[PDB]
Length: 134
Length: 134
Length: 128
Length: 134
Ligand SMILES: [Cl-]
Ligand SMILES: [Zn+2]
Ligand SMILES: [Zn+2]
Ligand SMILES: [Zn+2]
Ligand SMILES: [Zn+2]
Figure: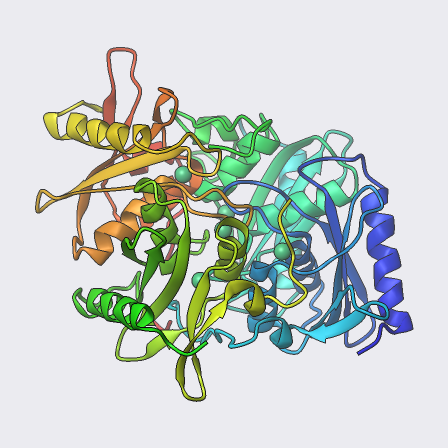
């Protein structure tokens, strides 16, 4: 699926966010997501060896705090003009479990594409969220 | 150290945030922190078995996105009208490593107290942040 | 890739592990991996809200402790006869970053198949 | 009060030391851990450094112990590579240990030799993970 105007806006928002702060090894990626009501949420990562969140997960916390229950699209943007970063595996899993069908923006052959997170986890592990077990 | 006026405001802010969203197993705690220039940032947790961030780590990402490099105080508040939660061990580590000397607000004998995160990790492990190693 | 004799031996090992221990509130999956020296390492998950490791990550730590530099295959077997579990997304990332080309054993149409971890992360994010 | 290092404690230091010394110096695998169960078996492992929260050595040990059917761990230590010696558990490890192995004693440095400290004492104003439905 090709990048929409809304997707380009997410790229632009996340780029503005990461470029708005000093270059840091700890806070090096911004993410923005849009809700089904059209609100945009953004954040930056927190790098730490105990599993500090990616930018996408910070965005999930910001959206939750705003009561935006349904997120439809999300992108991650690297610092220093480095562009789109695909979601890492952890981000894919958390997004598939908590926001099924959310589309992540990634680099593609003819231009950026918008890919449902489940397609980013072929042969998926689907957490049964009703239980505190794997 | 007894709770300060700014500390009470962080409690009030986090309380307002968590009680402003539907009760959820997954988005169940809010956090608020203040910067050295008086800016207050908030967020909610994202529970997930792959290590979804606590509310405190969402706040760190929000604060970083705003360019607030120095955070001085932080609190976490439970849902359903329910009050202060001390930081978990992971939050203590991340806070100690990334925001040295930040005070966490916790329950105390005469009222809430504000404790330097390092005092919440006796016999501390200090990450040498210059390296991708423990 | 169809399941190999080595992959079946790995499934036997992981199944033996999870079926050999009691029920717990904190674990539910065993994993086993193969090294390019023919070594096999196993472990069970550690469930915790701060990101306790999956079984596969425990296995990586056991491999590392043994000085085992290259792992070629891995599988995760759930308790209660639930069978093979595909790696979760975090496991895929760690495996791709630390053990490029490792094959995860997953369930496909004709039974278990073995799939390079990179194929389990289309449009991959590579840690620099 | 902290207990002085026991013979079993020293055997864990020796185990972790032999483990970490027996492998190539690496930034990804830089710490070994060893723990002893009530049934007297010793379990060991090395950390897996990764930005998605790859486990510390202690967490690997918990998985090793569980796979072996050893449900009760009483003492644990972490030994760093390059003769760097005892590392105290990080904040995440303290939380996981307290929640999963209450009363386990961590071996940490002391002014008069190493001491063995109940992990709850390493988390003043402790956060306890509480849910019967899940
Ligand atoms: Cl984690
Ligand atoms: Zn990520
Ligand atoms: Zn926490
Ligand atoms: Zn996993
Ligand atoms: Zn640790």
